[PDB]
Length: 282
Ligand SMILES: O=C(CC(=O)c1cccc(OCc2ccccc2)c1)C(=O)N1CCN(C(=O)C(=O)CC(=O)c2cccc(OCc3ccccc3)c2)CC1
Image 1: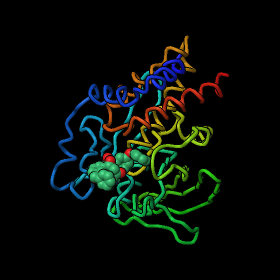
Image 2 (image 1 turned 30 degrees about the vertical axis):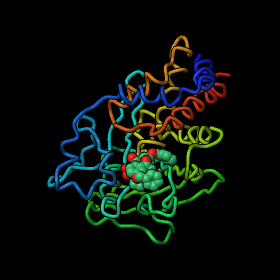
Image 3 (image 1 turned 30 degrees about the horizontal axis):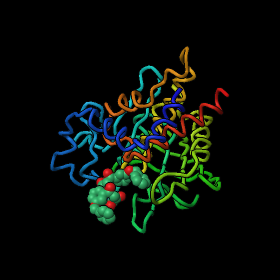
Image 4 (image 1 turned 60 degrees about the vertical axis):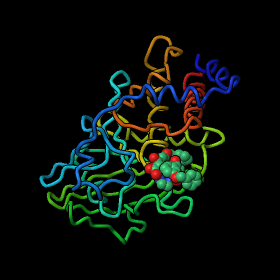
């Protein structure tokens, strides 16, 4: 299986080497639009842009740009939209996307503040009576309920298209315990968090793709989607041990750069998939 490979790479301590090959082999596509001058203030990181071929487009003239990519996993039949944590000026764009793409869930893998810095704008209302209105995209966001757990928080939000008065319920899954430095010691919490998102139906095909982000929307976001897809695959095909994490990761990297930012993140991904496979299929 992959656990053997995991214990192997660990034994020889070649994770960094394993990770480098991936980066070297990683796909390279143009990000022209993300580079246009008019979109400079719509990007969080200069080294984190969406490829033109898989970028999500806002359904509006003037500027259809948002730093978000559609990651379509054909075999696993699962799609994810990976994006950057909204900026003070792109919160309206962020929810416009959620609306236009018909997403049911938003997965947040970071805290608004980490390492003493703001890694993301406060894009959702923190109190029921203090709704948020996004004038530019003409949308209203209202906090309906909030369930705070030790490792994550789930919120029910009501998104209303002020233009048509139509409303939709959005589930916000906020993983709040990813350490400021490195990765979690054990994947237990992360897996439970993933299973929670799954059980909500937010990842199901009847809905638009789930929207995932952290700070750059690649490191933790990549780990989340990689783990989910690998587990699905091990559940769908004849021999589960045929699932090649590296292959899946390369496949995903064809849609957005940076997925999995460090060799430590890669190891953790293996660890999550391995442990998750034991829970799913004993
Ligand atoms: O965190 C880092 C470390 C890093 O690699 C980096 C990148 C470019 C320049 C740099 O100076 C040199 C330096 C070295 C050591 C100490 C201070 C300063 C450091 C950071 O100094 N920053 C975050 C965002 N940033 C950038 O220049 C980026 O734009 C980096 C990026 O791509 C990125 C941003 C958020 C998350 C992510 O991946 C998930 C993750 C979660 C937890 C731990 C490790 C990784 C990747 C500016 C400040």
